Length: 67
Image (cartoon, rainbow, N blue to C red; front, side):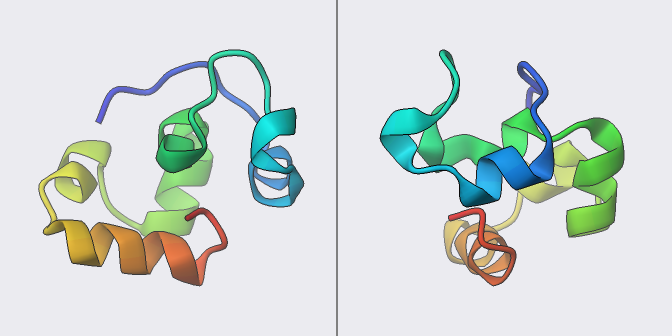
């Protein structure tokens, strides 16, 4: 629920895992979204998202190509 270095949504969605920027964990792409992008993509706070059951977090990310 802790925002890390920001990267554009397109970089996170269209880049192969091994080609992602230093420090970007492919399994935690949402933490690299800007606050604006996070709100636009998920429509909830990061804390709210992190408190969702894992299956829901994954399903939401899958629908957005962020899993």
